[PDB]
Structures are given as structure tokens and as C-alpha cells.
Image (cartoon, rainbow, N blue to C red):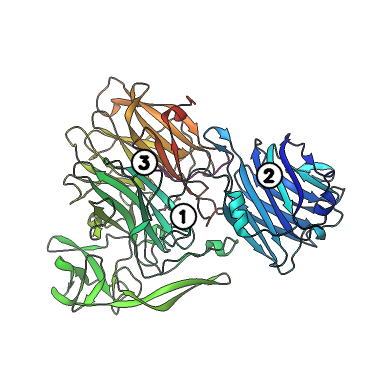
Amino acid sequence: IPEGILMEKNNVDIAEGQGYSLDQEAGAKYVKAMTQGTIILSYKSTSENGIQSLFSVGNSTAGNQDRHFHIYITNSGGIGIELRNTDGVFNYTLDRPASVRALYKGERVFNTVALKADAANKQCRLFANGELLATLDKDAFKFISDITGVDNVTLGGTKRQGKIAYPFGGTIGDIKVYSNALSDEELIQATGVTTYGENIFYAGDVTESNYFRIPSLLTLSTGTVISAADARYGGTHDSKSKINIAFAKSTDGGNTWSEPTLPLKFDDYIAKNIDWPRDSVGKNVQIQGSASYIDPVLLEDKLTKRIFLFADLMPAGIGSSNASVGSGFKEVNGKKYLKLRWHKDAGRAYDYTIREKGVIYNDATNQPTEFRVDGEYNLYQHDTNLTCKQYDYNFSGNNLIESKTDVDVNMNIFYKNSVFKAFPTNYLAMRYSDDEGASWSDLDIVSSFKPEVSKFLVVGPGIGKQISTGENAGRLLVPLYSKSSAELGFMYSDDHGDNWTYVEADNLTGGATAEAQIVEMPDGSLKTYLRTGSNCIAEVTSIDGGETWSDRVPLQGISTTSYGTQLSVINYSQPIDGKPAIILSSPNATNGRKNGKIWIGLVNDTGNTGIDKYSVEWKYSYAVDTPQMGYSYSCLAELPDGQVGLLYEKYDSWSRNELHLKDILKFEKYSISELTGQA
Ligand SMILES: CC(=O)N[C@H]1[C@H]2O[C@@](C(=O)O)(C[C@@H]1O)O[C@@H]2[C@H](O)CO
């Protein structure tokens, strides 16, 4: 077999289910006997078939349907290979979900992929659109030379018992087959020729996190665009993990973004880039003893230009699902204070409180102790800062080993090895900034109002809202949800963020994931759209600045799942078709987080008063990709130009098969012209 290119083809159109034979190519005899090599191809799929082989080599005869090698893509954006010679001899597979796309801005686009079969290193690697997607290691390295009875080289399908299986439909822009193993560098470069949308945060940036989730995007009145997201270190798992909140800004309308920062973070566990296992066992494992922050909300007070970042604060080993019932506060002398448990007391003996100036008091004696905390909640014993060893986490087989290192970090009340431990429920935290993220204020735990009967009271991720007109103009609002006397709730401030008041919006005690976002009506009244535990998105209205809310009404015509998915709904500054408009983003499928769509809702005055005053007509819907393509959490923002920016999870974040994927948080922009189908 010669060194270099064995076969090359260009601009090949393939009719769905027909495939294309490469048997007559001069190098077919070499390709049918490859001991290793590299395949790189550019393609555009126009088919909705489930599995679509791009290139294959194998045995087409009867009874030999399990003898072949093929590189394929799926209608849901997955990509992979299967190297087979019947299950008794070998069946090597490698894939990565949500690796490619089908449609971008209304048109089918080309993706560039590559498979490298490295005999010397006994390794197989898959690449797509400039990224290394997956790696397979095998002691018994195998390739085309190991398949019995190869009799064909085919494009757009895999020949099985004389039939075209895994039928592709579309165009193979280019294909090059090398007998040699090209370097990862050459393949990253070669496949990187086609990319769509951009990353703000990414595996390898200064956050040191390989994964991200829960997007927040907001254009400030100054023109600067800011964003935040969970920096999920231990895979894409929710809290009871190691998660920090990442932040970045753009001063050029969303074209380029600054180096990300970590405004909300904990140091009990080290922040590092780690590849979380995706196998059936390891994928379910998560960090057990780390404190974390989760689900960000960004908000701007246009009157003061101040910005706020909110997120849930989870004590060590705590998440929404295992949070203890209680406020985490104790009332002494009429004032609520954070309570603490001395590590040597009984398991549930929270006999201390953090009072004025961070001084820790003994409640039984009502006398101050020798301990105190700073504005970051780190402990001190007589002005001397307390410390503890930072933990590291590594997999030993399917087991996650969490061990102490020799690195000292300040002892914080939310850490598992702290001498004074906070109550194991969730808290609401926030910091403000007057210089667009250059510096942030001290940690402000605003959840003193958490109902003592609640398991958890958390934020609805995305952005908050400031009322611009009416009696309550200037009021700041942040959506919340809980498992307590109410499900949907809100916290508002009339003094520019200095103080917050909690509001129960219903009397539902089921604790469903009622993530909501708020939009303002022309007269200042508000409409909140929310995820529910039923097969619909609900709408509630307030005519008193968010103090009381109407009963839930299903949002007619916008399909969703029973478990649901977070949504984003924003006010647009200019009228569309002459009417005030709001824009909504959410996956449209009734099962699975996929088929993302952006809708434009036109506000109509019905002629009625009160809660029935306005009616929103969802006149336009825009499909971001094809129906099976992944789309989960998202956040919209009107950019300084007329465009609508979109930061979203381009995969199914609920699925147990799409956990721990790198670089799925994408940033895209769309004009109103595009969104209204007006080209
Ligand atoms: C505080 C918290 O746990 N937020 C979670 C919840 O929502 C998500 C989700 O993708 O649906 C992602 C959020 O980061 O998974 C969680 C689950 O639904 C339990 O509510």
C-alpha cells in the first residue's frame, strides 16, 4: 500500500438510499486493505434518515451484514464509526452526540469530519468542525485489513446483504483517504474550515472548566454585552458537584469576548480541566463533598447602571434534590441571622449565629465567640484566618476518589471540613458591580426570607427585570421557584438592590421546576412565562408590580415536554409589524430537548382592563436547525445593532446519553428580518 492519498473525490451528489460506488477508483484495491489510515470528508446532509453512513468499506454479501467499517452521522447531530467483522471477532465503536449540525440560518450547511486510525499508537480518533470529539484505545488494534471478504468501497451508505443500509442523502463535498495517520494538529486545522456560531466560554479557557451550562446573556444600557454560565467542572451534573459561575463581556456588539472571570466560586475543591467518563457506569458518578454555585441570573438597574449577578449557593455536598427543609436562619432579637453548627456538637445542633460585623455568637449564652467571618464567609479565630486542605478528584476505575492535597485554602462556612458549618439547605447569593465586571462587591446572601417550611427556594436562570413605567417604575425583580407553600415566586427590590422582598405567586406545594422569565407590558404590568411540571408553558400576569399574580394559563400553540425545559423571553425595544413585541426561545419537541425555535409575540390591547388587558399573538416561529437537533437552555438579548443574540445549549441536557459533552454552549445572532421569515 503506497504512502499518502489512496483515493480522493470531489462534489459527489448522492440520492437518498442510492449511495455511490467507489469500486472503480484506481486506489480501491488499497482502500479495501488498509491496515490503518485517515479519512477526511466534507458533506452536506439533506436527509432526515436516522443513521447516515458517509463512507464505508466492507463485505456486501449474504450473511456478512456485520462485516464492515463506516463513518456515519445521525439526524440528531451525532457522529461515529463502527469497525466490524461480526461480534465474535470484533465490534469496535466510537461516537459523540451533538457533534455536527444540519441547518444554519435557514440553509443546509457543510460539516467537515475526520477519522484517524493510528496503528502505531493503537488509537482511533474522531474530529469535526475543528475539534477532537472522541478517542478509542484498543490493545488489539484492527482496521479494514481485518474485515473478512471486503468487496466494496461506498459513499452515502453501507452495503449489507446487497442493500444500502444507513442511507445518506445530500452531497459529499470532498473526501480524501490516506494510508498514513495524519497528526491531530493537521486534522483540527483541516476540519476547522467549517464552524457555525461562536463560543464565549470553552474547554481550555482560564476558567479551567471543561463543561458549561445554564446560559445568561444581557445587553447593558451602555452597549456592553455581558454573559454568565455555570462552569461545571465534574461533568455536566447539577449541584452536589463542583460548579462556579463564569462571566465574560463584549464591547464590540457581541463579536469578541473578554477572558472569562469567576465572580462566584468556592475553593474547597480544585478547579481543573478533567474528562468525565461517558460510559454507562462512570457517567452517573458526581462529586460528593464540594460546595458550589448554580443557575445564574444577570440584571441591570438602568437608573444606577449597576449590574447584579445572582445564583444558588449550595453548601458542601448539597443540591436542590437533597437540600434540608428550613431557612438556614435563626431569629434572635427579632432579626434573622445565619445559623451555624460547631463541628463537635450533635449532628443537628445549630446553636450559633453570624451577627453584626461577621461576629459568631453562642446563642445559648448570647455571648460573642472568638470566631468571626469576613465578607466572603471565611472563618477567623482571633483575627487569624483559618485554613483547611483543598480536595482533588480523580477516577480510579469507575470510582471517583476525592482526596485532600497539601494546598491550603481559607476555611469557609459552606465547606465540609469547616469547624463551623452552615445549615444544609440552599441559599440565594448575589454580588453587584459598578464597573461592568472589573470588580464585584462582597458576597450578599439575600435568602433570609426563605420559608422555614421550604426544602429549596432557587432562581429561575437567565435574566431579571426592572419595571420601566407606571407606579412601580424602578422596581427590580428576580424570578424564583420552590418546594414549599408556593412553587413560582419572586423577590423584588424598591431600593436598587439594597433590600429584597419575597412573593409567593401561587399555592402549589409540588415543587416542580417552575423556572420563569419576566416581560413588561406597555403600561408597566408584567407577564411571566414559566416551565411547569405539565405538558405546557404557563403564563401569569401581575397588575401590581409583581406583588400578586393571576392563575396559570397554558401558553396555547407552543409545544413542550412534561418534564419541561427553561425558556427565555425578552422585551424587544422596537415595534414589529407596528406592535410592541416580545421574543421567546425554547426547544419545541414534546419529548427530548430538541427542535429549538425563536418566536415573536405581538402585544395586543384587547380593550379590557386589569389582567385581561393584553393578549400576545405568537405570530412568528423560527427553527434554528432541524427537528432532531439538540436544543436546551437558552438566553436571548437584543444587541446594540438591531440583532437578537442567542446563547444556548446545542444538545439535549436532560438526556442520559448526552451528558459530559464539551463546547456545546453556542452564541448566534439573528436579524428581525431573518426571524420573521422575511429572508
Ligand atoms: C437548582 C437546580 O438543580 N437546577 C437544575 C434543575 O434544572 C435542570 C434541568 O436541566 O432541568 C438544570 C438546572 O441547573 O436540572 C435540575 C433538575 O431539573 C431539578 O430541578
Q: Is residue 63 above or below residue 36?
A: above
Callout 1 touching callout 2 (CB < 8 Å): no
Q: Quadrant of residue 668?
A: top left
- Residue denoted by label 3: 253
Q: Residues within 10 Å of mark 2 (few under 14, many from 20)?
A: many
Amino acid carrying label 1: it is Tyr
First in sequence: mark 1 vs mark 2: 2
Residue 490 visible, this orientation: no
The residue shown at (62%, 42%) is 75
The quadrant in which the N terminus is found is: bottom right
For the point 74% across and 46% down, the residue is 8
Residue 629 among magenta residues: yes
Question: In what element is the residue under mark 1?
Answer: loop
Marker disc for residue 51: 2
Depth check: give the residue in front, 247 or 513: 247
In three-dimensional space, the C-alpha distance between marks 1 and 2, rounded to whole angstroms, equals 29 Å
Discs 1/2, front? 1
Query: In this orientation, which residue lies closer to the viewer: 483 or 670?
Result: 670
- Whether residues under marks 2 and 3 lie with C-beta atoms below 8 angstroms apart, the answer is no
At horizontal 30% and vertical 71% (from top left) the residue drawn is: 348
Is 162 on the left or on the right of 678, as rendered?
right
Secondary structure under tag 2 reads strand
Lower position in the chain sequence, tag 2 or tag 3: 2
The amino acid at mark 2 is Ile
Closer to the camera, 164 or 41? 41
Q: Is residue 346 magenta?
A: no
